RNA sequence: CGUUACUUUGAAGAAAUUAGAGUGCUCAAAGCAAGCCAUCGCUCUGGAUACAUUAGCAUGGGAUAACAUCAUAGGA
C-alpha cells in the first residue's frame, strides 16, 4: 500500500465485537485515539449493536451529533472513537453511566456504575521519565500524559484518575497479592490475585494469577491490570466476578435455569 | 567379523571370574612393578611384558596382582612408547610390505594387502588422534 | 554388529515361546531389558527371570509361562506424546482390551496405560501381548 | 582410653562403641599376634543388631586405608573380639563414601568407586571376607522382590557356615538388599 | 598502536584531551576508556575494559546494543577482519517419514578484539543492528574447543 | 558458573473455513440469532469451546539418545 488503510473488512474485525458474517462487507474501522484499534469497542458498536439506542449507521450519527454521549466526561461526536477498557461512558440525558470492562469470555461489557463511581477511571502507568525542562511526567496505556506524578509511582502501576479534576487521587503499586484483571489473551476478563512474578532478562515477563475459587493461570505483564489493593478491587465487577467457568459448569447453569 | 576378511573366528582368551590374585601368587606388588620397568627398559612392549610375566613368572595377570594395567604402570614411571604399540606393529607391517613391493612390482596381491594395512593404520591413527594419544599433526607416509 | 540388545532379547524370547521352550537365555543383559522384563512380569506375561553376573555384560534366564503371543521392539524409538499413544496402540496392539506398548519416559520405563495415568510421554521401546 | 576409636567428626561414641573400644584396649597386648599390628588400628563406628538366627551381630567400620592390615588380622581379631563379646558374630567392613549422581550442570568425573553399586559390591566382599565370591545371581520374583544369590567358595565353608544368616541381616541393614548364600 | 588507519580512531563522546583527568570516575568520563555491560547475564571481558583497541561495533566498548536473538554455534571461519562465520547445526524434522535430517546455517557475526577465536570454538552471539551487508550479530562469549 | 534432542505444562499461533455448544430460519442447506401470557418491558439474553505441523518463548522431568569432555583431576 501507499499509505494508511481507511477501511476495515468485516471478516478482519476484532472477534470480541461479535459482528455477524453477513451484515456487510465492512466493519467500523476505529479512529485513532486513547486505545488500540484491536483492543477497543467503537462508539457506534456501543450505541447500535449493544445498547440498541440506534438501529443504523446514520442513526448513530444522529445520536452522537446531538452531543448526547460523553466518554470519560467529554463529549465525543466521532462514531469510531476507540472506547476502551475502564472507560466511563455516560449519557447525561437518561442518567446512565457505563464502565467498559471485560467479561470472562474476552468481550467488552457495558457495566452500569453509580454516579459517584463514574467520577473516576483506573489507568495503567506505561512509563515514568523526565520530559522537557527536566519535569517528571507519567504516561498511561490509554494515552494520557500526567506531569508531576507522585515519585512513588512507577511503570506498570495503576492510578486512580478523577475525571472532574484530572488528577491522580490514588494509586496502586504493582505488587504480589494485588487483585488484577487480565485485559489480553485467552484469560481476558479473568480476575485474581498475583501470586508471583517470574522475570526473564531480555524477554516478556510472566505473571502468575490465582482467582478466588483457586484456579491458577499465567499471562504476560502487558496483559495484567491492577484493580485493587489486596483482595478488594477498587471498581465493581460484572456478574461473573471475573471467575471463568468451564463449559461443563456453564451447561450446569443452563440446565438449572431451564429446570427452574 | 574380521574387519578386512570374511573370517569369523572366535578364538580368544577368557579371563577368570575371580579378579583377585590366586593364593599361590606371593610376589609383592612393587616387585612385579619393577620387573615391568626392567622389561620395558630393554624395549619390550606391554603385550610381550605380559607374556613373559605369565609364562616365566608366577604372575597370571598383572591387573589382578597390582590392581593396574601394564600400560598404565609404564605411563606412571615414564616408559610408555611414543607411538602406541598396535600402530607401531601396523606401521612395521606396512613398511615391510612396501619394501617387498619395491622389490616385487608384479605382486598385485601384496598391493591389495598393503591397501588393507594402510586402511587399518588410518583407522587406528584417527582413533588415537581423537583420544589424544598421538600428536594432533601426526602423519603416516 | 549388535545394534539393539533389546531387539535380540525380545526376538529370542519370542522364538523360544513359539518353540514351546520354558526357559530362554538372554545375552547381553542391560538395564533396559531388565526394566522391560519387569513390566512384562508385572502384567503376568512371563515368570521368574534371573540375572547371571559374569563380570561382563550379564545373562538373563527367563521362565516362560506360555502366555506370550508376541513381543517386539520398535526401531527407531519414535517420540510418542501422550496424545499419540492412541494411534500407536491402534497400529501395534491386537485390540483395545489387551496388549501393552512399552515406553521410555523421564518418569521411567513403563507401559502405555501407566504412561497415560501419569500423563508422561517419551519414546517407544516396544510391545508385547 | 579414647584412642582405638575415632569418630569421623567429633561425634559422641555410642555406649556400645565405647564397650568395643574398651575391649580393643584390653586386647592390644594380649598375644604376640595381638600386638605389632594393633598399633596401626583405628575404628570409626561399631553398632550391634539382632539377627534371625537368635544370635546378634556387630559391625566394625574402618578408615579404608588400614583395611588390608585389618584383613591380615581379620581372622584372629574376629576370634578374639568374638571371645570379647561371645554370641556377637563380629564383621569388619570398611567405610566408603557414596556420592550423589552428578547433575547435568556439573562436570565432575565422579570416581566410579564412589558410586552406590561399586560401594555395595565392595561392602558385600568385605562382609564375607573369610570366604570368596565365586558367583553372583539375582532373582526377580513375581511380586517385584529382588533377591540376590551369592556363591561362596567351597573352601572355607566351615569358616563361613553359621555366619550366613548374620551376614544376610548385616547386608540387609547396612546396604538394603535381600541376599542368600550357597556353596557350589 | 591501535592507530592503524588513515584516521585517528577514538571512542565517541570521550574527551581524551581533558585537563582534569581522573581514574575514579565512571567509564567515558575524565578521559577514561568507555565500556558497558551488554546485559543478559554476560560478563564484560577484562581485555575490553583494559584494551587499547577502538571498535565501534564492539558490544562492550562500542556503540552497538545487543537486542533480539541469542544464538549459540561453532566458529566455522575466522579469515575476515573482525568478522567470523558462525555455523549453527540443527535437526530438521521431516513430517512424512517421522525422521530428522541434519541442517546447518552460516551466520556472520562481528567479533571484537577482546576475543581471539579459532575455527571450531563454541561461540555465543547476540543480535545487534545491521553492521554490514550480511552481519547482524556480535560475539558475546567464546569457549575454546579444548 | 556442560549443552541438546525428547517429553510435560503454560502463553501465543487473525477472522473466515473445519470440528463442535446453544438456538424449530415451517424442515434443510443456513444464519447468529433469539426467548418470555403479550411485558411502555424483562432474561446482566446469547453471540461457547476445541483444533492449529514446524520454528520461536517459558515451566517441570532426565528414562532413552546425541555432542563435548572424561589421571599434569595434578582435585579441593
Ligand atoms: K507499503
Ligand atoms: K587368535
Image (spheres, coloured by chain):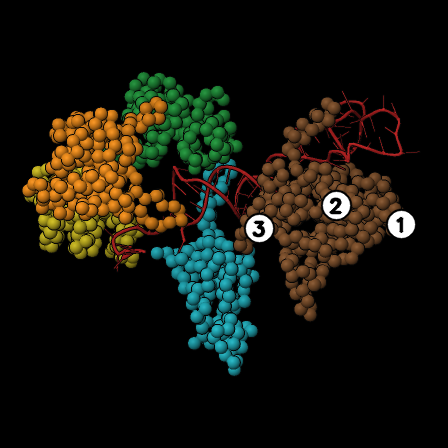
Chain colours: A brown, B yellow, C green, D orange, E cyan, F red
Task: Give the mark, 3 or 1, whose residue is nearer the N terminus.
Answer: 1
Which is more toward the observer, C111 or D154? D154
Q: Say which residue label 1 marks.
A: A66
Which is more toward the observer, B104 or D106? D106
Q: Position of residue B45 (x, y in %)?
A: 15, 50
Pointer 3 and pointer 2 on the same chain: yes
**Cα distance, mark 1 to mark 2?**
22 Å
**For the point 48% across and 20% down, which residue is it?**
C97
Which is more toward the observer, B83 or C107? C107
Chain for disc number 2 = A
Label 2: element kind: strand
Q: Position of residue B66 (x, y in %)?
A: 15, 45
Q: Which image quadrant is residue B8 in?
A: top left
Chain for disc number 1 = A
Chain for disc number 3 = A
Furthest residue toward bottom? E19
* Res. A14 mark: none
Q: Position of residue E58 (x, y in %)?
A: 49, 66
Q: Say which residue label 2 marks.
A: A100
Q: Say which residue label 3 marks.
A: A205
- Decide: few, some or many residues near mark 1? Use Cα within 10 Å; few <14, some 14-19, many ≥20: few
**Cα distance, mark 3 to mark 2?**
26 Å
Amino acid at each position: 500500500a501507499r499509505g494508511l488503510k481507511k477501511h476495515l473488512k468485516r471478516l478482519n474485525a476484532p472477534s470480541h465485537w461479535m459482528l455477524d458474517k453477513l451484515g456487510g462487507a465492512f466493519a467500523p474501522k476505529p479512529s485513532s485515539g486513547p486505545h488500540k484499534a484491536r483492543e477497543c469497542l467503537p462508539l457506534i458498536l456501543i450505541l447500535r449493536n449493544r445498547l440498541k439506542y440506534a438501529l443504523t449507521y446514520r442513526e448513530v450519527q444522529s445520536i452522537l451529533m446531538q452531543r448526547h454521549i460523553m466518554v470519560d466526561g467529554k463529549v465525543r461526536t466521532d462514531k469510531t472513537y476507540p472506547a476502551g477498557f475502564m472507560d466511563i461512558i455516560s449519557i447525561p440525558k437518561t442518567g446512565e453511566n457505563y464502565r467498559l470492562l471485560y467479561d470472562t469470555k474476552g468481550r467488552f461489557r457495558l457495566h452500569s456504575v453509580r454516579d459517584e463511581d463514574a467520577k473516576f477511571k483506573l489507568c495503567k502507568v506505561r512509563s515514568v521519565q523526565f520530559g522537557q525542562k527536566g519535569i517528571p511526567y507519567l504516561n498511561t496505556y490509554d494515552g494520557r500524559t500526567i506531569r508531576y506524578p507522585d515519585p512513588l509511582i512507577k511503570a506498570n502501576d495503576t492510578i486512580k484518575l478523577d475525571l472532574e479534576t484530572n488528577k491522580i487521587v490514588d494509586f496502586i503499586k504493582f505488587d504480589v497479592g494485588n487483585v488484577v484483571m487480565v485485559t489480553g489473551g485467552r484469560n481476558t476478563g479473568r480476575v485474581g490475585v498475583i501470586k508471583n512474578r517470574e522475570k526473564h532478562k531480555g524477554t516478556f515477563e510472566t505473571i502468575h494469577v490465582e482467582d478466588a475459587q483457586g484456579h491458577q493461570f499465567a499471562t504476560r505483564l502487558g496483559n495484567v491490570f491492577t484493580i485493587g489493593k489486596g483482595t478488594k478491587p477498587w471498581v465493581s465487577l460484572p456478574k461473573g466476578k471475573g471467575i471463568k467457568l468451564t463449559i461443563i459448569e456453564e451447561q450446569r447453569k443452563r440446565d438449572a435455569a431451564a429446570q427452574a | 567379523g574380521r574387519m578386512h576378511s570374511r573370517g569369523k573366528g572366535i578364538s580368544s582368551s577368557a579371563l577368570p571370574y575371580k579378579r583377585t590374585p590366586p593364593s599361590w601368587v606371593k610376589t609383592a606388588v612393587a616387585d612385579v612393578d619393577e620387573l615391568i620397568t626392567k622389561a620395558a627398559k630393554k624395549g619390550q612392549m606391554p603385550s610381550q611384558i605380559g607374556v613373559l610375566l605369565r609364562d616365566q613368572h608366577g604372575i597370571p595377570l598383572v591387573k589382578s596382582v597390582t590392581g593396574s594395567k601394564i600400560l598404565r604402570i609404564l605411563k606412571a614411571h615414564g616408559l610408555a612408547p611414543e607411538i602406541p604399540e598396535d600402530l607401531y606393529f601396523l606401521i612395521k607391517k606396512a613398511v615391510a610390505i612396501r619394501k617387498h613391493l619395491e622389490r616385487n612390482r608384479k605382486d598385485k596381491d601384496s598391493k591389495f594387502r598393503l591397501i588393507l594395512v594402510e586402511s587399518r593404520i588410518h583407522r587406528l591413527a584417527r582413533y588415537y588422534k581423537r583420544t589424544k594419544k598421538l600428536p594432533p599433526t601426526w602423519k603416516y607416509e | 554388529v549388535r545394534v539393539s540388545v533389546l531387539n535380540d532379547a525380545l526376538k529370542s524370547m519370542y522364538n523360544a515361546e513359539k518353540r514351546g521352550k520354558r526357559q530362554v537365555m538372554i545375552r547381553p543383559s542391560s538395564k533396559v531389558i531388565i526394566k522391560f522384563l519387569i513390566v512384562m512380569q508385572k502384567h503376568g506375561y512371563i515368570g521368574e527371570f534371573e540375572y547371571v553376573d559374569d563380570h561382563r555384560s550379564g545373562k538373563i534366564v527367563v521362565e516362560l509361562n506360555g502366555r506370550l503371543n508376541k513381543c517386539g521392539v520398535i526401531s527407531p524409538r519414535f517420540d510418542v506424546g501422550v496424545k499419540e499413544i492412541e494411534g500407536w496402540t491402534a497400529r501395534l496392539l491386537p485390540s483395545r482390551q489387551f496388549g501393552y506398548i512399552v515406553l521410555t519416559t523421564s518418569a521411567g520405563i513403563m507401559d502405555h496405560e501407566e504412561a497415560r495415568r501419569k500423563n508422561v510421554g517419551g519414546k517407544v521401546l516396544g510391545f508385547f501381548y | 582410653a579414647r584412642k582405638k576409636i575415632q569418630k569421623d567428626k567429633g561425634v559422641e561414641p555410642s555406649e556400645f562403641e565405647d564397650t568395643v573400644a574398651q575391649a580393643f584396649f584390653d586386647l592390644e597386648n594380649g598375644n604376640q599376634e595381638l600386638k605389632s599390628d594393633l598399633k596401626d588400628l583405628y575404628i570409626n563406628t561399631a553398632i550391634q543388631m539382632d539377627v534371625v538366627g537368635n544370635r546378634k551381630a556387630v559391625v566394625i567400620h574402618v578408615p579404608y586405608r588400614l583395611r588390608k592390615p585389618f584383613r591380615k588380622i581379620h581372622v584372629r581379631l574376629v576370634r578374639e573380639l568374638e571371645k570379647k563379646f561371645s554370641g556377637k558374630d563380629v564383621v569388619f567392613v570398611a567405610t566408603r563414601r557414596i556420592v550423589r549422581p552428578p547433575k547435568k550442570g556439573s562436570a565432575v568425573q565422579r570416581p566410579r568407586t564412589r558410586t552406590l553399586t561399586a560401594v555395595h559390591d565392595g561392602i558385600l566382599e568385605d562382609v564375607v571376607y573369610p570366604a570368596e565370591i565365586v558367583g553372583k545371581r539375582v532373582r526377580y520374583r513375581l511380586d517385584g522382590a529382588k533377591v540376590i544369590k551369592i556363591y561362596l567358595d567351597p573352601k572355607e565353608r566351615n569358616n563361613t557356615e553359621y555366619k550366613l544368616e548374620t551376614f544376610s541381616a548385616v547386608y540387609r541393614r547396612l546396604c538394603g538388599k535381600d541376599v542368600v548364600f550357597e556353596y557350589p | 598502536a591501535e592507530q592503524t588507519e588513515k584516521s585517528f580512531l577514538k571512542q565517541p563522546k570521550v574527551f581524551l584531551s581533558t585537563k582534569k583527568a581522573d581514574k575514579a570516575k565512571r567509564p567515558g568520563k575524565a578521559g577514561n576508556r568507555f565500556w558497558k555491560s551488554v546485559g543478559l547475564g554476560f560478563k564484560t571481558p577484562r581485555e575490553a575494559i583494559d584494551g587499547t583497541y577502538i571498535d565501534k561495533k564492539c558490544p562492550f566498548t562500542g556503540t552497538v546494543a545487543i537486542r533480539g536473538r541469542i544464538i549459540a554455534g561453532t566458529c566455522h571461519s575466522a579469515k575476515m577482519n573482525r568478522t567470523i562465520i558462525v555455523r549453527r547445526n540443527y535437526l530438521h524434522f521431516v513430517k512424512k517419514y517421522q525422521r530428522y535430517e541434519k541442517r546447518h546455517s552460516n551466520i556472520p557475526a562481528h567479533i571484537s578484539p577482546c576475543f581471539r577465536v579459532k575455527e571450531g570454538d563454541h561461540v555465543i552471539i547476540g543480535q545487534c543492528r545491521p553492521l554490514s551487508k550480511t552481519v547482524r550479530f556480535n560475539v558475546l562469549k567464546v569457549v575454546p574447543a579444548g
